Image (cartoon, coloured by chain):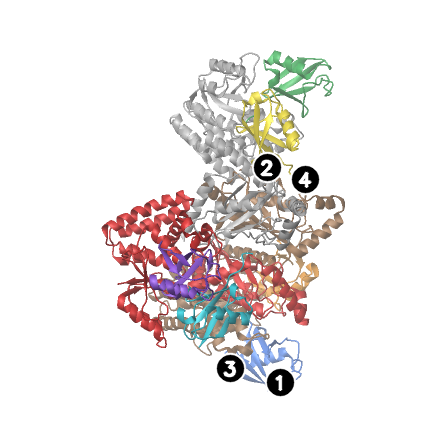
Chain colours: A brown, B red, D purple, E cyan, F yellow, G blue, H orange, I green
Amino acid sequence: GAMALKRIHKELNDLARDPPAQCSAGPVGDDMFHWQATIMGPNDSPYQGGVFFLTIHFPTDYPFKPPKVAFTTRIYHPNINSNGSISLDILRSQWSPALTISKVLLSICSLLCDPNPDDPLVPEIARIYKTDREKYNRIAREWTQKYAMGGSAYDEAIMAQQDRIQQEIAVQNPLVSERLELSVLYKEYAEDDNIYQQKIKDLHKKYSYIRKTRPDGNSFYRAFGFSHLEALLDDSKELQRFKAVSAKSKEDLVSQGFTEFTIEDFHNTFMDLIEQVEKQTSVADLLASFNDQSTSDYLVVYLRLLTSGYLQRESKFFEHFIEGGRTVKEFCQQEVEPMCKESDHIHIIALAQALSVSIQVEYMDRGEGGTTNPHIFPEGSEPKVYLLYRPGHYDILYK
Amino acid sequence: GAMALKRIHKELNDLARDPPAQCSAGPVGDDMFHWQATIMGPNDSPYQGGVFFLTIHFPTDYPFKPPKVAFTTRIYHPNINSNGSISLDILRSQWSPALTISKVLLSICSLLCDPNPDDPLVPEIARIYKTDREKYNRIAREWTQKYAMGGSAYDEAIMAQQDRIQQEIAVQNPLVSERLELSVLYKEYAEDDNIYQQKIKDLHKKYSYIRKTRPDGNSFYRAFGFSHLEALLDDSKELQRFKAVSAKSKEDLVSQGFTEFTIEDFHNTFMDLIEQVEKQTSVADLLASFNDQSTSDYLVVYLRLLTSGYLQRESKFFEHFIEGGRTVKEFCQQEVEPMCKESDHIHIIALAQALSVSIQVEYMDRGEGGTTNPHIFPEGSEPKVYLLYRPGHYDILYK
Amino acid sequence: GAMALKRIHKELNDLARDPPAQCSAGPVGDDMFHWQATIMGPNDSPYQGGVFFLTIHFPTDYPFKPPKVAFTTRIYHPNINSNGSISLDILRSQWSPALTISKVLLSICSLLCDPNPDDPLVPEIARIYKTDREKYNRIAREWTQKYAMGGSAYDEAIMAQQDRIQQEIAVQNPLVSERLELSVLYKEYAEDDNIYQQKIKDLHKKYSYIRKTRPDGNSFYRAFGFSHLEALLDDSKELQRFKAVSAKSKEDLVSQGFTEFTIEDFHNTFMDLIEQVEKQTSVADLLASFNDQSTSDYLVVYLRLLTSGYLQRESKFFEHFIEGGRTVKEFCQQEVEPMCKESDHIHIIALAQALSVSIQVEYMDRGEGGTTNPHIFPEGSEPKVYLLYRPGHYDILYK
Amino acid sequence: MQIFVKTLTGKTITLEVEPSDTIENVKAKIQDKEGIPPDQQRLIFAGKQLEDGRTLSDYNIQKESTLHLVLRLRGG
Amino acid sequence: MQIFVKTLTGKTITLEVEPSDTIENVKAKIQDKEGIPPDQQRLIFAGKQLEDGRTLSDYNIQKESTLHLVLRLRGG
Amino acid sequence: MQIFVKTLTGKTITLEVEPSDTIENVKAKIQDKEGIPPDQQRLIFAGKQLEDGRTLSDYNIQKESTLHLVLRLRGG
Amino acid sequence: MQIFVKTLTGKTITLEVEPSDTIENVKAKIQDKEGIPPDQQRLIFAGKQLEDGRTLSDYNIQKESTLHLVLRLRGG
Amino acid sequence: MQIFVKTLTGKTITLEVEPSDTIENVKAKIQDKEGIPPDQQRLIFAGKQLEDGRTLSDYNIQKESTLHLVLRLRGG
Amino acid sequence: MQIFVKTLTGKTITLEVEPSDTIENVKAKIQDKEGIPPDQQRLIFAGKQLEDGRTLSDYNIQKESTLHLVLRLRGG
């Protein structure tokens, strides 16, 4: 009940504090007493390359009784039956209330590299391991190849990898940084690197300030959105037109075959973001909105949706502009609609034409001169919104 | 967390709005993030006649990550491994947050009729399907015959069918309609049908108003109950006697071998319904009570329980009045105690004698005259509660 | 709706009221709609000696639809397929809302001793049972031997046994009884037993009062703790020193390799118990604290932790004082750290030296004289805390 | 021979018949006394529902046997 | 006058009937098409269970209505 | 002087003992009946674990008390 | 022979080439007219991204064929 | 100038590279070590997806940086 | 020969024995000095609990060996 739950929360806090890369576990959806463990086959095992899942059920009275833990993935091992039950005794008779689920976890992870043919759960496998190790390693490798390597497991594992990566990225940079003097860019690069440093000089010629965004894969939509709202933070009529077209855009999308109730929320977040800018609030407040996870992300989703919408609407125009044999809608389903997918030139033109707005992008990679060349595309317009492109990443520029 | 749950609720709303007959899904008991899908083998498949179950786990962060979906039922197919993992990529890399679980569902349902030997999950089955279709169809049919046809499955499938049917019925008619001029009945029948129309004339002679009920199988108990409470909505002494006998009825039932704690709740709903009528409230309020799902249904359950109780109490009287070799208690367990089972004359007499009350029923089918003959059974009494019987359905009549 | 949940709670109440020893069921962790049933193979079956698990999923609408129940353990039987589905029809067509999950349970338990070759789920097994009973019994016994006898279930079964036992013990005695005249001890023993009665006379010589504790396995730590706090309920300086050493003890433990966040809660309960005694409250209040389950138990856990801590700290001293080839830390992990494990002399000396306090124990078993000899161990001290040892059980004594 | 038929309401009716009388004929004879139209009648003799085509001696209904009258009335 | 009946799959059958046709007659036509014996059939129109011996006209089944075929499965 | 001991199943064994009998002696009688080796036995009276080398009289086990047989299973 | 290249902005450019001209050469010829540096250019002929080393007749680009210009610009 | 690349397991590979090396060149060295085909590789530095045809110096990968190997798995 | 026995309380006792002296005899000799009755004593020599029947040279206890005294005291 009460203290059991509280304790479970404490344990999850501890496990989150010092995350194991090889074996981690956590609650399934809503349920606190039901956890799923993902443990990786240790290198220098037969189990190497495999991904093993466990289920963990915390008794209603906890810590006083040990958690019930079992492998869902089949595994060849003297201490684990094909029924899935784990035979180490800190899970049965030797369990103290002072023990942690983490201790149990690395107890099992340890049990993998170093089995225990002393008190075997599976007499035959014990015999094989104790006598002929060749056969044991071979069989275990085959079982890993079959049961632990499936196209499911691997999806979950890679998902975890991604999450770790942009969690580190998350703690590194905020979604949208405060307005920064771009002299800071000088620090990002080595003094050993002359060419980049001097292209930063050339960028310093044209622009006074820079606003960084997270390298989360959505950086273009995030930057584009923020800078383009902040642009109408003052202009009276532009806010009106933008609000109008953005309002009609939902109807266009719904009419284009998108299910209304799903896109309705994202549209709502978008329009609310236009609402904070409607009667002008200082840039810091809408920035505070953009640094909230789900609000910003919802906005990104909607911008991607608009992008895909206009892409499919004009589809016979873009059709020859895309590499590969993919159709336009396939391209939308793959490289635009889903989150965290990288964006390209096509995306920029599409979103720009979707909101009917102007964009300028400063390309900085390796120049023949220090010159970083601009790209303005509505064709030959006079854009008031500026973005800095460096390879793999978009940022905001302020003149 | 939060918005994820809200979204899941929205998706369930959408899926409930336009129910698929072939493939539907829904939450398991309490859990919102754990759904079970029941998908029927499409006709003109090898999978025809089979019933396939899926499990669906919504990630704690939703829509941002795709739901995890897998077949629990084994199936022969190039895109689904015997591990159960589904290989279409709207579930992995191509997932947009704007997609619905319904889209996924009919994506799989589509994947059944039209497999995908392009990017196979199971290379061998892919080879078989791509080369020799005979063997594929044959094997797939055998696998369906084995795994998908079990005595567990068909029950669940038919359950789903029933649920779909009375969901449509539910959206069609309310549990208890407002008091209606019975001229409305004229609309229910074709002008082509003379005999019925004229029997409606004859019914118009005797009765001014009509109150319809849902054709859910419980219509008799629902109508009987509502009209008989509404009858005591005024009469002072009758309410008292009815309340007394209904109160003692619980004790009689408990003494008759029914487990008290179960029937206690139903008895409570019943007595509360007598309580709303105790100090008179306008008919509209108790009607509002009768249009609540679980309250009305609980009442129906209790009325069925009373019916069964008095049926078994007097059992040697009714014993020869029932078709078949069934005993009286078997008849109760089959045709009365369970919900949604049709009711007959025996039920009416039993319930009437159980509450010691009067009932009149107007039989309207096909007359030799326009005459729709009444049936009053306590024998030769003067009933103040009137019901209209049409084949398969009971309704309330108001003089 | 929620009436479903309420009902489930009522059913669990009923099932807990009159517990079946052979077949019981209950919720899995947090989830109310997901239950696990443990049903024992009845004696005079082939299934004798086996332990069979069931899963029970209550439909979101309950009682109106029957619970979904299935064997997870494989079983040989004409009415249960190796798929796990149970074929009795109170689970399908014959289900009344007035039925209880208990009725279902003993319906299945009954289905084990007396199968039903009338309407078979598994035609072949039905044929075998109906024709050759030898083969049926033999096969069924083999299947029991394989699937139902595993090292995974037996743990759960024995766990249940233990729980039943100290539930009866719990309802028998409170964790800590009120201060009692020890004349009550005269009642505990038969008049037939002279030797014990006279040793009670001799105990009556030395001590006026007695305070009993639960025979739960923790009785020593419980008694020791309570009496030693109640001892400082007055003394001013002793409370200070005890509080100091108990406060430092946590740091010593954490430094000794115990994970801090786990032992932190137990330490907190301990220090709070010292806090209730800090500014003196009457003995009855701290007693009221000791009769709360989890508070008292948390305290016991911490005392065990201290015991283990000082045991490992001085380990090379105690090393030769322990029977068996176990090392000291193994002895701690086995006979001290876990709950409900019996305590010995080693435990007492260890805890006493851990808190640096004095203890006296009156040994009463069978004397040559009436003499019950005292044991005071800090060596030759003047202990103000007294305990009564009878075989298998510790109690508190008041001079 | 004469026959007995017990209604579900508790009433008992005596009828004038012969072994060769059809079931429909008897239902008409019930309509005479109790005023209930034949197509609304289902009568049972010892657990068996009697079909309209058959006669009395078909179901082995002898002198002074007892029938049971129930109304059609199946709904939900 | 033709009628529509949906099966468990969502598959729809079309049938040639007249308002005066028996229900068991309809079950028989369904048997002629699908192969499901009549006794394994339970028909539903507008939430109402259809008695074997009645007629479509009795249940107010008009031109192009939609029926439901629910299979009563032997209890096994 | 006879004693009662419940097993894991709820099955009760009756035993012929004297108050001066050893616990291991009792475990031995239980072995003679059920076949469970003494070392696989752990006996419980009134929540108390019974030492092998003590006597019933030591634990206050009087006529017709109820014991408990809990099997310590080898850790596998 | 002369060639066509359509920019994503909607613009269309005509170029002066020969079948043996390398892709890099052509990208330079685009830099002349539109001022876009070669390393920022990705041009596609019928779904296929053209590699800098190859010539025109390598990809089977004939007289009056149409290319498609897209900027590098991949980020997130 | 040497670089570090972490795989799915948390396993770290060390690589001998120069700032002017192609990304596909690096993917190729990783293939030479682990055996993972280059097309099954997706490399990540500082949250940025690395284009096959660019150079380490383009992405500001300096001495002893840490890369990430994420496997794009065929959709099965 | 004389012997050493260390109590758990920290105390150390010297005893007067010979190799043929039984364990029970020694426990009595401990009862003389420390006043603790034999049946309450469990003494250990190098990890092994000494049984009452055996002598000293049985367990190979030589001159000036050290025993360890612990009380029976097992409860819960």
Q: Residue A173: horizontal and vertical position, in percent? A: 49, 57
Marks 3/2: CA–CA distance = 78 Å
**What's under tag 4, amino acid-wise?**
Asp
Callout 4: SS: loop
Task: State the residue in front, B397 or A326.
Answer: B397
On the image, numbered disc 2 is attached to which residue?
A93
Q: Are marks 4 and 2 in one subunit?
A: yes
**What's under tag 2, amino acid-wise?**
Ser
Which is closer to the viewer, label 1 or label 3?
3
Q: How many residues crowd around disc 2 within 10 Å: few (fewer than 14), some, or many (20 or more)?
A: some
In the rendered image, the vertical position of residue E17 relative to residue I11, given as above or below? below
Q: Residue at 39% of width from left, 57% of height from top? A: D5
On the image, numbered disc 1 is attached to which residue?
G17
Residue B375 visible somewhere in the drawing: yes
Which is closer to the viewer, label 4 or label 3?
4
Callout 1: SS: loop
Asked if labels 3 and 4 touch by Cβ distance under 8 angstroms, the answer is no
Q: Which mark is residue G11?
A: 3
Marks 4/2: CA–CA distance = 14 Å
